Amino acid sequence: SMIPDFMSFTSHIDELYESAKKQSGGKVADYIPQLAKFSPDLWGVSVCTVDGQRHSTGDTKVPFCLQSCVKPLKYAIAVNDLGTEYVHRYVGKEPSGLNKLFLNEDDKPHNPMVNAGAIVVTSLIKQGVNNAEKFDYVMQFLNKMAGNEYVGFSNATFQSERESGDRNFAIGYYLKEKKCFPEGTDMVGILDFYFQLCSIEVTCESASVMAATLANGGFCPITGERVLSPEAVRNTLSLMHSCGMYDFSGQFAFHVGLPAKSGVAGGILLVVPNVMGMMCWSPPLDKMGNSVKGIHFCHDLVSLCNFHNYD
Amino acid sequence: SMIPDFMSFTSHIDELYESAKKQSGGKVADYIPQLAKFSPDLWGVSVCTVDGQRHSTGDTKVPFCLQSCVKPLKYAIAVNDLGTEYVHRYVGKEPSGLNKLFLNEDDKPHNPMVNAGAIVVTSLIKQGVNNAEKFDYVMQFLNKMAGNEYVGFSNATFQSERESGDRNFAIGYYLKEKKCFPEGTDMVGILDFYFQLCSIEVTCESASVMAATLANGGFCPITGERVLSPEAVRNTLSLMHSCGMYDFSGQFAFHVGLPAKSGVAGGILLVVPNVMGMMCWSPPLDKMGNSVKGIHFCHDLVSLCNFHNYD
Amino acid sequence: SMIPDFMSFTSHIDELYESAKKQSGGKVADYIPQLAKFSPDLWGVSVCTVDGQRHSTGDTKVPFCLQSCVKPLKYAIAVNDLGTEYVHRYVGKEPSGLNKLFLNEDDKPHNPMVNAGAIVVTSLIKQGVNNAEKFDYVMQFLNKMAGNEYVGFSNATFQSERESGDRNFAIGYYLKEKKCFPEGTDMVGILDFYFQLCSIEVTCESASVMAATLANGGFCPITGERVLSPEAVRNTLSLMHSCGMYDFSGQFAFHVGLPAKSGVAGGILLVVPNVMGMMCWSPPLDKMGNSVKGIHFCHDLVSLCNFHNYD
Amino acid sequence: SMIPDFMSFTSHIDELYESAKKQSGGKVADYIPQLAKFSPDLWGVSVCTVDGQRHSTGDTKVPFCLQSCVKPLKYAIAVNDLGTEYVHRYVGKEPSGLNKLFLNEDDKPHNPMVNAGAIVVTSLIKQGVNNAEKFDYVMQFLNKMAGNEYVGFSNATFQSERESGDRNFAIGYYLKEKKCFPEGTDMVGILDFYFQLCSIEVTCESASVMAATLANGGFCPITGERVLSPEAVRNTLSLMHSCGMYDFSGQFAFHVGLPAKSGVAGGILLVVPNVMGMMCWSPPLDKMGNSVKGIHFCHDLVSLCNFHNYD
């Protein structure tokens, strides 16, 4: 551990937080009202070490949707219950070029971090049981990852995403055309389960616990229990490292060097292997679709604490 | 007219027909039973001059679905009722590269001869009225083009295409995502109208009359009536010339030089400007998706009668 | 012939010429001084019917480089001496998608109308003999096409194109890498021959005679002699129809419907099959790289005289 | 350090070495004789810890060309003398899609690990001085990285690469066309310097010392001296992680999780951050172009010692 004095570290976290606060650029997602609602000034950062030590600053208790931030999580869950080999017969393992085809060279979604990928992954989890049951399974799972902290749902977001995601339906039908789903999959039913997962709510605080779980080889820092298999955690981290920041993934892997995953709600699930989990949140996104204050913060954290993968 | 002696010409048509008959290669489409049914040995060629003169050989009275062969026709109808400018605010005017994106540089289907294009075009025809009425409108229209000859429908084909076209639905949703349809379009309703049009039935004989209509500047050779506007006919011919033979369009424009349009049913709508209309039909298709006997025939017709656009 | 009264037709040509004259937009090519020199106001149109009848208006006697306009010509020459089959073992027969790869699916230049294509074609003509001799062979050939009218050379242009064409050298080496040239080809020597051909000079008047030759099935309208084989002329026309106006080829084939070929010098070699040959010239080019006044003129000519391929 | 007992670790290295030895597949590069020469049975593995501890097994003293393995090294050198900002005004920082364009969206080579990238990087090192001097500069540099161990040159390889690299010349001219080189660069001279660098020779033993240098934050394990800046080492490692195994980079980052770089000579420069440097060598390559025995070994090393970046 490179964090000898937590107290001092925390003091630095608040300095970075304050430094980022001055970054007012970016635009709040507004393709649906449930996202337009949010104030551009909300800005929260929560830390949770592998030690179990916590620290928050800013709006770390205001609920918000995981959206794309859930992709790493449901993928981790799939590997946990099905293993690397099986999950990857349906989804790739690397970033794509850039326009934006749904499938790769082998008629499989490039990776679990893109829509097509997350949709296929969603179709692997808890096959057989009905949607209601599948959703409880993932919720219970997310609860263990967060050590029983805040994990809600947003029905308004769910209804808006469903009655608006024409591109996800396009992807749904295309994958069904290319036989990308396991035998006998209710494609439309899957997209529904998919929209629901994107609607799960968390707070910087509860999310940081989930990130810390991934930073602690699958053991929840605040309960000590094994939630995800070592295999599942290593895969999730690798993929977050290469494709978790949309079109910014390259720049991010080169300059920040940490496993992260952004969401349109403005959140950024950050993981510092064997050190801590983190969740930055600020609604204003840049052109790439990442939280402006969040990206700023991440670069600052790595310059200051030499947390970069290769330091 | 390069056909001084119709009698002799006909004798040559039968020779080419017999020559093509020996081409047994190709595979009959079988993605649906209604197409698998067909015998690979069916082979028919019907001619209809701008003069009104007719001639058939082979299975020219066995009904079969137009399928893609209807694309040029419904496009002609759109230009006829809306004019070049309007129709092309929604669909392109040239062939694409090759994989196979749904939209081009300007978020419009490349041309009316590809699925995405034909789907958008379908959404322009007779806007407002219900589907049943739209279908009668096109049927009545196709009747005038065929001079009241055989124009049927295949409900079995229609039902199979609908409960099987996942890729067309994918295209449907994608176009709806990119705002490619006119304001307030029932996308799913349009795909239904689209599947129905693909299910319209004709015979080499009735189809050749439709082709002759396009070969006669919009006037049906056997009734003398104006069916399509000059503007509409010129557009349809240009596009059939550059993108009517799927991936073979280039080779076809270079070696045959005639406006044509193939269909998965094995038909090839051929037009020899100011001379005649033609419909070759033979279920076995090659890798490109064109009738094997039909392609052979077309090359032979141009070598023998110097009908190539630039002879 | 749709030109009953040449006198009246000529009167219309001058009206279109005057109408186009008002189009002052576009920018004169300036990648080399020999092209920057030209006045944006130069504008000439020369007609030469299959009959042998002539007519000029504007700056039809000011020499200018063929540049890309020579591509159709040297291609015609290759087919004439080697036949379709041989020439096309090295170059494609259709337009490409759009970035801009040097080779297609089969490691062959897409068509003779693009740089890579024209370079490969250049390597087929008069193999064996030295460059000086090859150049005389093509010059003598171009002379017959122009009926002995103006055909010059521009050494200043040649020297500038050679000491500046890094992209053509890149293409040269790439093709050499993919074994695109006939056995034992001096690649660098070929690029030199290529640059020279681009530097050949003509005038609207002499060029229109060359165009008329292609419009007359290979027979020079003003000498009556056979210059190009029927086979060679049909191929050249087909390719000019689909890929002779750079990225505008699609729009041009759909709206104008005539075999044409533009050049960076501002010229447009136009052919109206079995009617006449033409050469419009005006240095200012549009974004696509075609003569602004020339494009305007071509659209006007087709609207007024219904010369479109499918009228 | 996860290597408590070096003795035991070494015993495991020899077991993996022996296990890999049984992998006889792959084909020895043969585009030039200097590579065809090599026996498919040569197989060597050399380790060099950050501690300075060494260990070899197999043909670890047979000289071979770095080839692509030098790309990470000359890139490290550029960052060391010019800093991240400057070097990256000319070359990208991420993997590309897949065909294989020379430049990316911003007209810059995708990254330093691809030919176009390595060529641009080569043009940044020691600008001004002549080629002979530039080469000595890099040689002296490579010597410090190897702690003065074997670093040779192969004139036969150099001469063959130069008189055979048409694709590198194509790339050279294209980059020169797009103004990718610093002001006043002798492009052809640069390609020469480039071919020379690819011809530098090493042995598993000396190379492993170079890898260990990168594994030790820029300090040569066997001399203790600072050779590369921390900044330069972190960049080199990140890029080796994402694009050092050609088309296998994705699979490699996901399954092995270590910074590596392969070469057509059959070598694989491997780095285990803060632990050791390594060089596996075996001439037979797979379709991707990586050493077959080397790839096998790398997967085995990570399964056995949990060296994967995220374990």
Image: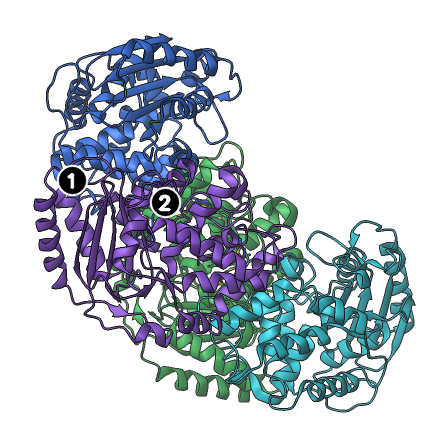
Chain colours: A blue, B green, C cyan, D purple
Could you give the CA–CA distance between mark 1 and mark 2, rounded to whole angstroms? Answer: 34 Å
- Please, what secondary structure does the residue beneath circle 2 have? loop
Foreground residue among A200 and A7: A7
Circle 2 residues within 10 Å: few <14, some 14–19, many ≥20: some
Foreground residue among D120 and C131: D120
Give me the chain letter of mark 1: D
Residue B53 drawn at (x, y percent) = 55, 76
Residue drawn at 90 percent across, 63 percent down:
C14
Q: Quadrant of residue A86?
A: top left
Residue drawn at 30 percent across, 8 percent down:
A7
Residue C214 drawn at (x, y percent) = 72, 79
Give me the chain letter of mark 2: A
> Which kind of residue does numbered mark 1 sit on?
Asn
Q: Is residue C102 visible?
A: no
Foreground residue among B67 and C31: C31
Residue B168: image tag: none
How many numbered tags mark residues here? 2
Q: Quadrant of residue C309?
A: bottom right
> Which kind of residue does numbered mark 2 sit on?
Phe
On the picture, is B222 further left or further right than D112? right
Residue C94 drawn at (x, y percent) = 54, 68
Residue D49 drawn at (x, y percent) = 22, 44
Q: Are marks 1 and 2 on the same chain?
A: no
Circle 1 residues within 10 Å: few <14, some 14–19, many ≥20: few
| Residue on which the image places disc 1 | D306
On the picture, is B110 further left or further right than C204? left
Q: Is residue D86 above or below residue C48?
A: above
| Residue on which the image places disc 2 | A102
